[PDB]
Length: 51
Length: 61
Image (cartoon, rainbow over all chains, first blue to last red; front, side, top):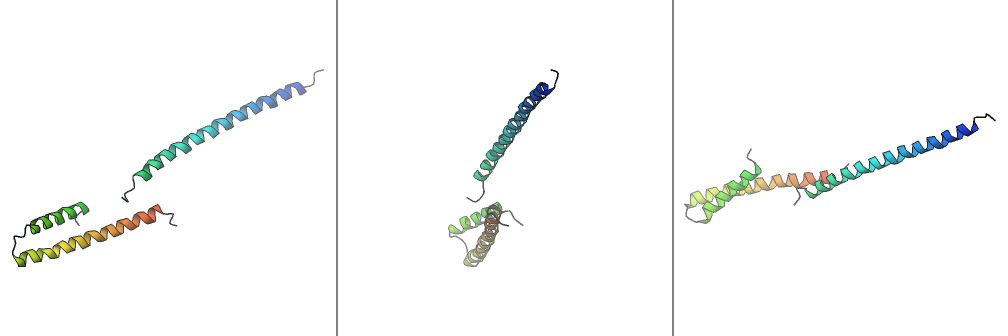
C-alpha cells in the first residue's frame, strides 16, 4: 500500500507546469525586444541623407 | 579646407556681385575662373558622398 508511484506522478505534472512558465516567459520577452529594435531601425531609414 | 556650406556661401556671393554687371572685364572675367573652380570642386565632393551611401545602404559584401 505504501508504494511511491502516486507521489512520483504528481512531480512530473508539477515539473511540466514550470517548463511552460519558462518558455512562454522567455519567448514573450524576446519578441518584445525584437519589436523594440525594429521601431528604431524604422526611424533610422526614414532619416537617410540621400534626398 | 573649407566646409561644404561655406562653398555655397562663396559661390553665392560671387554670382551676386557679378550679376549686377558693373565690373571691369579683366576683373569680372578673372573672377569667373574661381566660380567654375568652386562649382567643379564642390560637385566632386557630392560624387563621393552620393556613392558612399549606395555602398553602405546596399547589401555590399
